[PDB]
Image (cartoon, coloured by chain):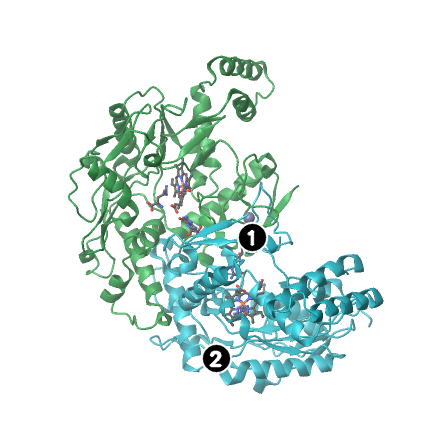
Chain colours: A green, B cyan
Amino acid sequence: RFLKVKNWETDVVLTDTLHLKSTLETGCTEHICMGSIMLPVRTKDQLFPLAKEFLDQYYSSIKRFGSKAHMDRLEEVNKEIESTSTYQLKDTELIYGAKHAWRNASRCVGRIQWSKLQVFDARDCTTAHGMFNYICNHVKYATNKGNLRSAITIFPQRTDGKHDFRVWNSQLIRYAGYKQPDGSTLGDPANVQFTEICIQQGWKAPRGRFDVLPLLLQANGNDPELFQIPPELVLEVPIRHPKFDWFKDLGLKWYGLPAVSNMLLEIGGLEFSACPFSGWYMGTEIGVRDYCDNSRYNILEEVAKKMDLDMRKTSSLWKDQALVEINIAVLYSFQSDKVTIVDHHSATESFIKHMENEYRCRGGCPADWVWIVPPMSGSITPVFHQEMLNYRLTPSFEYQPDPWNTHVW
Amino acid sequence: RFLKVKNWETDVVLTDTLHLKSTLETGCTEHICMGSIMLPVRTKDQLFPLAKEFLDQYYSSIKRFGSKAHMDRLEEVNKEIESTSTYQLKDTELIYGAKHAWRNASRCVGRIQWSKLQVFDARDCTTAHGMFNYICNHVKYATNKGNLRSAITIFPQRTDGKHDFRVWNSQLIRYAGYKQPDGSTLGDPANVQFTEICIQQGWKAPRGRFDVLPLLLQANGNDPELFQIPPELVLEVPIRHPKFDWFKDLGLKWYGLPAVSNMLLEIGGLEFSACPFSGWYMGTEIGVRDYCDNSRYNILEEVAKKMDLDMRKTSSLWKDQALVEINIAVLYSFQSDKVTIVDHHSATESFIKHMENEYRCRGGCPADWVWIVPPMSGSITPVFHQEMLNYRLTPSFEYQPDPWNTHVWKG
Ligand code: HEM
Ligand code: HEM
Ligand SMILES: C[C@H](O)[C@H](O)C1=Nc2c(nc(N)[nH]c2=O)NC1
Ligand SMILES: C[C@H](O)[C@H](O)C1=Nc2c(nc(N)[nH]c2=O)NC1
Ligand SMILES: NC(=[NH2+])NCCC[C@H](N)C(=O)O
Ligand SMILES: NC(=[NH2+])NCCC[C@H](N)C(=O)O
Ligand SMILES: [Zn+2]
């Protein structure tokens, strides 16, 4: 019932009671753990309970659990569901839900900032052009001249599933990926398929290495449209090294605003299929994953060469040595240009603090170790030695099929 | 029920059917994953099934399933069980059992070597002095002057739980740890409690930074006894760096033979509480964990200073830079002294090949991602990008309580 988690470096032991309020499944079973697997419309009857569960936690959060207001609201929503087969959240409920979906995101190491989320209610939006406007405003607000501010923009909830709002991009801002005749890949291999669905749509791609993709926005279930994010709104950082002047020659740059846009936000049974959100980068995301993954910009060898390291045998740890230098470059570049960014040591330390805060004020904190531990220097960060319990709490952010595999033009 | 795992770097997808043979539990439920939790006597009733299961797997592997030999053996065992409440494994079965416990060890990244395990049958052992001798032979055989060979020595199985054989040490070779009155620790902090027990039992502690601990051996449920491993049998490697001549001045060194000695080997329902086993090190075990964990030797700062790195702000990644150099030092020193060792890049690439092979020839490979991924440079090793399924098959190696917590002292 009550589970405990120990940190093997500090001996601190926490008791988890929050998992008792878990609803959704985890992919795991008493017989098999799938903790390392990346990816393990509602009816009136289904919706009622979800809405009730949500309202209970909401009113409980405002110290009005069981109050007339609570009962009234519950009755009101109940009537609305029976009638409209769905319901609308109050602005207050919307903000609470979004903040909590972030609070409940077990794979996010940056949750100590959860309560500071800026919520942009775009539920009144009706067209793709309207979505573009809302998105540009989000980008400008969150970028804030490099002094990044977390934010989320929430478009209209799902209805019948044939009038869904969707942002086809996986991130508001990402670099293009095109398959060369050379057999190689120019730009970001991760975005080849999406890039081709755009280019196909008429996008005149400079067919370069770091070309900002266009937004492909889908409003009310209609076919998506393209738009070029005002260049003046896309903050980018040229990557150079504090010691290797040849580094800048590598010709590397990355954008400053990480804005996941293909997820689905669920609050009280309601599904918000277009809910782009953004925060700021943890260095390793760019330096380790985006730059060094073999299926991404895969730049290790080239950097190793420039460093003139013995790349004859893996045991010289040339990959490791290079990895560190690259990551030092990313952090240096961002910091130099006054753009918000956090190193993995600092971020993990704050997550440990957040976990403790969460355990005492809330009884726990769902966390996915596989995702929380940074992709480099694992055991050198405190989270590596921290036992974590992963479970699903709602409101939540969920994965959802890429639209081009569901859309019917 | 077929379960598929995908590698996100190569798109290769594998199907697992082997998990169906899993009967033990994981600690997880459909509502909570305990994948990152370190630690999530039998009766005739329960022993019969366990024995049959094992013998069936054994006879199938030798292509004699259903043979008369298979049937007679089952008959022989059950009779022996009802007759004595337990049973004895044939030599062949023990070897098969030990090899498979290794093959089924989900936290081990070195399993591509599972079939080459050298098994030493020490089931005829009756005393602690006898255990010492078997252990000395195991160390000399496994060390092989630096050309390490994997081995395991198996002492008598548990009977009534009152006559257990146990190796009180956590590893056959490990350095003492001493808590100082000023609160600091001399040596290895992970072994402070065991070191205290040794001293209490009579060990005269040299009180240095790298003192090899004495063996504390328990035979047949009796109080444990102390033995010193012949120094000439303990291979050590002074740690130096190929470019930084001051590294050697840190006075670091480590032993070459990693030999876990506190786990329990379960085969056919039988429990072998003393089953020390050894392989060879993956560099990061020493370089990242033993040397850089804050609760171990914790040398990152010192190394960092000597390298004159900006230690004012973490964003300099001075911790990361020093960590890399230290691991370069460990590999280089072992290679120079011609002592077997494998870097994490090489070991993980080998595990991926082993895992794919296992899926094809066995239908799966239980693996604990949390343990398999190296403690440094995770994503630049292939295992990071590999989805894995964690489940428990027997034969298996299991954790067991430290003996000082359960032992009934005879005096
Ligand atoms: C303020 C700075 C923030 C930091 C430093 C941070 C950091 C991280 C990191 C490093 C990851 C893993 C990224 C990856 O490997 O792809 C992550 C994942 C995630 N974060 Fe945060 N985050 C921040 C803000 C946000 C915000 C504002 C939200 C939502 C409102 C959020 C929701 C999530 C979710 C749901 C995931 C998992 C996404 C997936 O499964 O791909 N994060 N975050
Ligand atoms: C041949 C060389 C070997 C290599 C390179 C190898 C490598 C490793 C490594 C890197 C670990 C993680 C250790 C830690 O973090 O403490 C591990 C764990 C493990 N290995 Fe292997 N191993 C080898 C041989 C063996 C042998 C001979 C056996 C058994 C017969 C074995 C049984 C296990 C088990 C059961 C664990 C988990 C131990 C625990 O929970 O503390 N390994 N191995
Ligand atoms: C297979 C495995 O789940 C996958 O390679 C992982 N991806 C990620 C991870 N962690 C983060 N933060 N992001 C990932 O994409 N941990 C492991
Ligand atoms: C809490 C967490 O499970 C613990 O810190 C871990 N220990 C280890 C690990 N992996 C290995 N190989 N060895 C460990 O001791 N992964 C994580
Ligand atoms: N810190 C964040 N909000 N990250 C969101 C995902 C960004 C992704 N990991 C990237 O490297 O582009
Ligand atoms: N490769 C092995 N067999 N390792 C066994 C565990 C050794 C332990 N991790 C150590 O650093 O001492
Ligand atoms: Zn699990």
Using the rendered view, name the quadrant where residue A65 is placed: top right
Closer to the camera in the image, B143 or A8: B143
CB atoms of marks 1 and 2 within 8 Å: no
Q: Assign a secondary structure to mark 1.
A: loop
Using the rendered view, name the quadrant where residue B246 is placed: bottom left
- Can residue B261 be seen from the camera position used here? no
How busy is the neighbourhood of tag 2: few (under 14 within 10 Å), some, or many (20 plus)? some
The residue to which callout 2 is attached is: B237
- Please give the chain letter of the residue carrying mark 1: A
Q: Assign a secondary structure to mark 2.
A: strand
Residue that sits furthest to the right in the current view: B83
How busy is the neighbourhood of tag 1: few (under 14 within 10 Å), some, or many (20 plus)? some
The x and y percentages for residue A391 are: 54, 41
Residue for point 71% across, 66% down: B271
Residue B321 as seen in the image, left or right of residue A128: right
Q: Would you place residue A219 above or below residue B198 in this image?
A: above
The x and y percentages for residue A110 are: 42, 42
The amino acid on which the numbered mark 2 sits, given as a three-letter code, is Val
- Can residue A103 be seen from the camera position used here? yes
The amino acid on which the numbered mark 1 sits, given as a three-letter code, is Asn
Closer to the camera in the image, A366 or B58: B58
Q: In the drawing, what numbered circle is on residue A7?
A: 1
Give me the C-alpha separation between circle 1 and circle 2: 31 Å
The x and y percentages for residue B220 are: 78, 73
- Please give the chain letter of the residue carrying mark 2: B
Residue for point 17% across, 47% down: A208
CB of mark 1 near ligand 4 (< 8 Å): yes
